Length: 255
Ligand SMILES: CC(=O)Nc1nnc(S(N)(=O)=O)s1
Ligand SMILES: [Hg+2]
Ligand SMILES: [Zn+2]
Image (cartoon, rainbow, N blue to C red):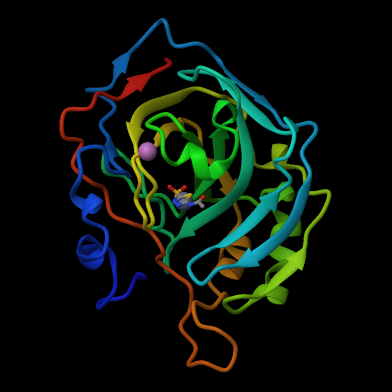
């Protein structure tokens, strides 16, 4: 599967029939139809103990991986019941600044989207959490092009080392708190992974406020490759899935 004409999102249903399911992601967030729900609690992001391990180009995005053997970096509160552990974060971006996010807000696309993936610890490991309707919680953050985000720079600087598919580099002591917006206001709805296998195990929490990154920072993302070393070079750009039918789900807003 991939993102090109012949293996892109419109073809994914043939190998993963869940592509046409009832709670697929991403979706367009219509701000006027979202329901303010006053019983939604504040989010609790406790990332002071986080331990990053490595950064990896996996052929469709680059992931920073975290040590999740202990409650080191956790998400709770919000719409969640239970503690969810951070296992990795990745981005989806475009070839041009006016496209790149997966979720849109009143049909507006942003330059990129950050996903911080968490799994529900009551299920014991990640592989069990993908068997449950509330197994995962992904925190989504929009990126707009503007001033440099200083906290993103270590990530941008290592990208040359993992240019092609399969490469990795040790990436310790990166603090994910430098990627968070000021406000933790959010929208939440029940959804899925946005890449195959597209499992419907995710409570999505999409933050209202985007973070700014510079043009130079998002250009470095665009220099990555989909292909492996020694293959024809395919630039890793536009690795996003288009919005899916909300199909009678309700988007709740914390504000
Ligand atoms: C192993 C893993 O994390 N897989 C994911 N697949 N899609 C994801 S996304 N784009 O919805 O955050 S995370
Ligand atoms: Hg599931
Ligand atoms: Zn993602």
